[PDB]
Structure formats: structure tokens, C-alpha cells
Image: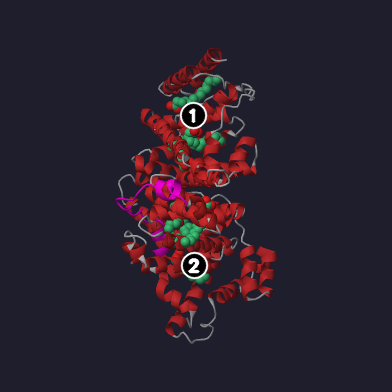
Amino acid sequence: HKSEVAHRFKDLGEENFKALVLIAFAQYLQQCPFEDHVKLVNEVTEFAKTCVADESAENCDKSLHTLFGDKLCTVATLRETYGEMADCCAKQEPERNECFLQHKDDNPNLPRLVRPEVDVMCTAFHDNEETFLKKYLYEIARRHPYFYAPELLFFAKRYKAAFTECCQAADKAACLLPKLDELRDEGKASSAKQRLKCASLQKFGERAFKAWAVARLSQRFPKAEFAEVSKLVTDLTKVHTECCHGDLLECADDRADLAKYICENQDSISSKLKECCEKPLLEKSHCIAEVENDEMPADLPSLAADFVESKDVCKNYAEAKDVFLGMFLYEYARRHPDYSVVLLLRLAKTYETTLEKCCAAADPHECYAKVFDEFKPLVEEPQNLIKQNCELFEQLGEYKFQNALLVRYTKKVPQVSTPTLVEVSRNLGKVGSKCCKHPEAKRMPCAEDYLSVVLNQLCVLHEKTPVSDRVTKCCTESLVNRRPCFSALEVDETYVPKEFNAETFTFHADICTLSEKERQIKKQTALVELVKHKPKATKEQLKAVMDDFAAFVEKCCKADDKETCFAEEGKKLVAASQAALG
Ligand SMILES: CCCCCCCCCCCCCC(=O)O
Ligand SMILES: CCCCCCCCCCCCCC(=O)O
Ligand SMILES: CCCCCCCCCCCCCC(=O)O
Ligand SMILES: CCCCCCCCCCCCCC(=O)O
Ligand SMILES: CCCCCCCCCCCCCC(=O)O
Ligand SMILES: CCCCCCCCCCCCCC(=O)O
Ligand SMILES: CCCCCCCCCCCCCC(=O)O
């Protein structure tokens, strides 16, 4: 293209252009104020219009990287506020952008973004809508500089819909606060999801990612031929390889290239991609990534023919092992959309281990004739774990299901900090509530996606403040073995109970005048410390202590004098539980 800036403006549209340029500036210049960035965005946008007007205008033939880096290098405070990052301007084009990207600070030390009160938010939404959402877009971008810029925009667009709807509702807080929470969880999950994919790419290599890709693409596109899924695995692998490097423009191009190829070959890939492929270039690749699984062919035979009983199984394996294993993973995944990707990866790993051992034996065909039986216990293990917990979720609420996990996982790794234990257990129970509402066919893929988010957060929190070697092993093993490693955690018998601290089990009147969440988290914090103090306590004893606690908190703010009931009745509750335990 003659003018790269002109085309992107022509296709993104002015609004998408300014917002993406705002995000881009924020992720590079994370310390500059909002007003400074708006000025750069407007200047870049005004210049972009000259290129749309005449692509031959001055500097309109420069590349986006060149033009973007020039504007960064015009910042007056570059050396004062970012220091070493101002040395990037002494370099040009390839080396300059790579220098700037290297100086992206993934975790800057900016203050916590406080969510204002609803009435303040709705008033700022109406008095200045553009400035309201745009500043927040700037605040999030600068705090997540590797967050893919379109997805960051895509979430921001949904925030406007939440405010428009709820700011005119009867109970605005009842409408808005849940939606802001879903989006905030949706975004933090997505952020952790791509950074996790990149770490796994560089920690376990391209081969392991290509295995994961065959499984995920074959489930999604089960009518697609193996040669087709294979080609899409290689392209998607280069896309993620480049996007993990971190340059927005090359990532956007690689994603748009693949999203274009898939859309021009829908007849050979999937039926579900028409609506996605009619969306603008900005949304194409994101839409395709969220497309639902296509229906698999009706009468597909079992895999026993080509992979177990047929002669040449070892011959076809040894001529090109990753081709053969890829064919096995493709055939298995496309028939089992109800399996998690890591489950199918466990299956291919077992199939690979069997062929390697058996093809070296005297009678290989006899050695691997029973290989399909080795898959069953691997398949049943998550399926049974889903039913135990979803049945447990049906019996209890989401809250009381969280309380069960609270007790369960405190006994397994009691060394984990109480805030991490409360947060991760609350999140795990929420994985239950969401995924246990899906029929059997959709339960395990649900759990894998949302367990990967919760467990990674657990492993992120644990990496920075190590406290348990077993959790470290689960966090450093293959992602395929992550969840089964955590599910293999047994109760820590070497733990010595934590010493009783009366102030930890002392409650004041603040508990009854608290938000439903802080009230739950404070009750759940006291539950963790209760288990940490009497770990060998049975469920009848604990249920008895939680039952007396329910009446204790129910009555002390059901009385005329609330403040001192909590200390006097708390002295009654704690001493009785002390005797009822140990
Ligand atoms: C990542 C997309 C934009 C994120 C900014 C949220 C939308 C701005 C309106 C203010 C909402 C408060 C944000 C929050 O507390 O979750
Ligand atoms: C006949 C066309 C050749 C296509 C080759 C595709 C190879 C797929 C790579 C993924 C192999 C996964 C094997 C594994 O690690 O378990
Ligand atoms: C740095 C140049 C300023 C404008 C930013 C270019 C737009 C980035 C996203 C382009 C659309 C990518 C769509 C996709 O993910 O496939
Ligand atoms: C982080 C999303 C990667 C962007 C490239 C995806 C291009 C469309 C292929 C989507 C097929 C499913 C692969 C996936 O799970 O992301
Ligand atoms: C507290 C957990 C609630 C949801 C129950 C899910 C337990 C089974 C997860 C195993 C399937 C995840 C993917 C896998 O490991 O194959
Ligand atoms: C750090 C406390 C341990 C964290 C617990 C991680 C377990 C993830 C859910 C595993 C599936 C639910 C049932 C199980 O543990 O077998
Ligand atoms: C050893 C001192 C005993 C006090 C320990 C109190 C433990 C609080 C359990 C949390 C209450 C669960 C019931 C609920 O939140 O509805």
C-alpha cells in the first residue's frame, strides 16, 4: 500500500483508529498523563486524514512503525520520565521499535484503579461520555501493555453498553455492578490466557503447541480435512509466535492474514464462520476465535482401524511420527468436542508412549492391541471429578460450595496464605457454578478453560511468594499435567496446626454493616484460619462451629446493643468451639 496509515484509517474507521492509537501510545508510554496522549492521538489522527485525503502527501508513504516511533520520539519528557527508553530514539526503524518494545514494562507500579461510586460513574458517563471511557481505556492499556489492542477495545465497547443500560435503570447499582464485575473478570482472564499461552510456547516449545493446536482446531473444525487442520496449525503457530514477541502491528497482520484465509476457505473448514467472516477486519480474527464448534460428520468410524488393528501402524508411525500422532490427535479430537484439550493431549501422549515401546517389541501389533483400554481411566478421571463437584455444587449453593473447597484445599496445602486460599477457592467454586450449568457434553471443555485461568493466577501468586514445593511442581509441570497434579494433592500430614490467636477469631459490629462480598470474604477468611488451627477436625465438628457462628452473627446484630454482644457472645462461641475440637 502507498500509505499504510491511510489504508488502516480507511478500514478501521476514525473511531477505531483513534482508540487503537490511544491504546498503542498508552502501552508504550505508560507513565505519560491522559492529556498528553490525547494530544498525540489527535495529532496522529489529523495527520492520518491528510493521507486519506492524498496518499502522496508528505510523510504519508512512511510505514506505521516509522511514523509511530517518530511520535514517541517527539515526547519532550522521554528521557526525564522514561530515561533509558529515550535512547531508543538514537536508533532507527527495525532496531528502534524493537528497543521501544523491549522497554515495555509489563507490571508498572501505578496506583490501584479505584472504581468510583455508581452515581459518580453515571454522572461522568453522561457529562462527558467520550472522556469517561477513553481515560479508562488509557488506564487499563498502560497497566496491561501486552494486552492485544483490539481485544482491549472490544471489551471497552461492551462497557458503554453496560453504562447506557444501567445508568437509566431503577436500581443502577444492581444493574451496573454485576456487569462491571463480569467484564473485569472476562478481561483479566483473557490477559492471563494469552500470557499463559506465550509462556507455554517458550517453556515447552513449538511441538507441544502444535499438538495443542491440532486438538483445539480439530474439535472446532471437525469437517475439516487433516491437511487443512495441519495447515491451520502451522499458521496459527506462527501467529502466536509473533504475537508473543509483542509488536501489535505484525501480530494484527498475522492474525488478519489467517482470518482472511479461513474466511476464503469456509467450505473446507467450517459452516459456522459466515457471520464472523462478514464482520470488519478489526473483529474477524477475534470472532473466529470464539466461533462455536461445527457439527462433526454423522457416521465417522472408530479409530481402531487405522491406529490399533491395521498392519503398518508402526510403519506409518515411524515414517513421520508427528504426522501420525497429529492424525491420531486430529481424529480423536474432532470426534470428542466434549473432551478438554489437555485430556486429548494426555491420550496422544499415551498413544505415543505405547507405540514407542511396542514398535520396539517382538510383536508390536500384539503389544499395542489393548492401547485403547489405557485411555479409559484417563477419560473417566476428569468426568468423575466433574460429577462429584457438580453434584456437590447442586447440594450446596455456590457460597457453601466455596466453603467446602475452602476446607478441602486448606487441608491439602495449609502453608498457602489465607488471602490466596480465600481468593482461589472462591474462584474455583465460581468455575463450578458456571460450568456445572452446562450439559455433560460441554462441562469438561468449560472447566479446562476456566480452571486454566484460576490455576494460573494461583501459580502466578505462588511464583512470586513460594511456600509449597508440591504447588511449585504443579505450577512448573506441563500444562497438560497441571490440573491432574493439583488434583493429586493429598492432605499435608506434616503440617503442625497454627497456634490459636483470639483476635483472628474476634468479630465486631462491622461485619453486619458490610457489603455481601466483604461479609462473605471475612466469614470465609475466619473459616480458613479455623481449619488452619484445627486441621484434623471432622466435618460434623466444623459444621457445628459454622452453625453456631451463623446464630452468633445472626443474633448479635439482631439485638439493640450490637457492639458488645459480638465480644461477649464471641467469647461464648470461641471457647465452646475450642472444646468441641482437637
Ligand atoms: C478494558 C476495557 C475498558 C476498561 C474500563 C472500564 C470502562 C470504564 C468505565 C468505568 C468502569 C470502572 C471499571 C471497573 O471498575 O471495572
Ligand atoms: C500429511 C500432512 C502432514 C501434516 C503434519 C502435521 C503434524 C502435526 C504436528 C503436531 C504433532 C503432535 C504430536 C504430539 O506431540 O503428540
Ligand atoms: C500502530 C498503528 C495504529 C493503528 C493500530 C492498527 C490497528 C491494530 C489492529 C488491526 C486489526 C487486527 C484484527 C485482527 O486481530 O486480526
Ligand atoms: C489469541 C487468539 C489467536 C488469534 C488467531 C486466531 C485465528 C482464528 C483461529 C481460531 C481457531 C481457534 C484457535 C484458538 O483457540 O484461539
Ligand atoms: C471446583 C471445581 C469445579 C469444576 C469441576 C471440574 C473438575 C474436573 C476438571 C478436569 C477437567 C479439566 C481439564 C482436564 O484436566 O482435562
Ligand atoms: C492452592 C490450594 C489448592 C488449589 C486447588 C486446585 C484444584 C483445582 C480444581 C481441581 C478439581 C477439583 C477437585 C480435585 O481437587 O480433585
Ligand atoms: C476457634 C474459633 C471459632 C470461630 C471460627 C469461625 C469460623 C467461621 C466459619 C465461616 C462461617 C460459614 C457459614 C457462613 O458463612 O454462612
Whether residue 273 appears in magenta in the rendering, the answer is no
| Badge 1 element | helix
Q: Nearer the viewer, residue 319 or 159?
A: 319
Mark 1, ligand 7, within 8 Å: the answer is yes
Residue 267 visible in the snapshot: yes
Residue 236: x %, y % from top left: 48, 61
Which residue is disc 2 drawn over? Answer: 254
Check the image and report above or below for 16 versus 133: below
Residue 287 forms part of the magenta stretch: yes
Residue name at image x 41 percent, y 52 percent:
331
* Front-most of residues 438 and 143: 438
Tell which tag, 1 or 2, sits nearer the viewer: 2
- The answer to whether 154 appears left or right of 568 in the picture is left
SS type, badge 2? helix
Dot 2 beta carbon under 8 Å from ligand 4 = yes
* Residue 152 in view in this figure: no
Figure coloring: secondary structure
The segment highlighted magenta reads 283-311
The answer to whether residue 201 is left or right of residue 171 is right
Q: Is residue 441 above or below residue 216?
A: above
Q: Amino acid at mark 2?
A: Asp
Determine the CA span between mark 1 and mark 2. Answer: 49 Å
Image quadrant of ligand 4 equals bottom left
Point out the tag, 1 or 2, that comes first from the N-terminus.
Answer: 2
Q: Quadrant of residue 413?
A: top right
Locate the C terminus by quadrant.
top right
Residue carrying label 1 = 523
Q: Amino acid at mark 1?
A: Lys
The location of residue 254, given as percent across then percent down, is: 49, 67
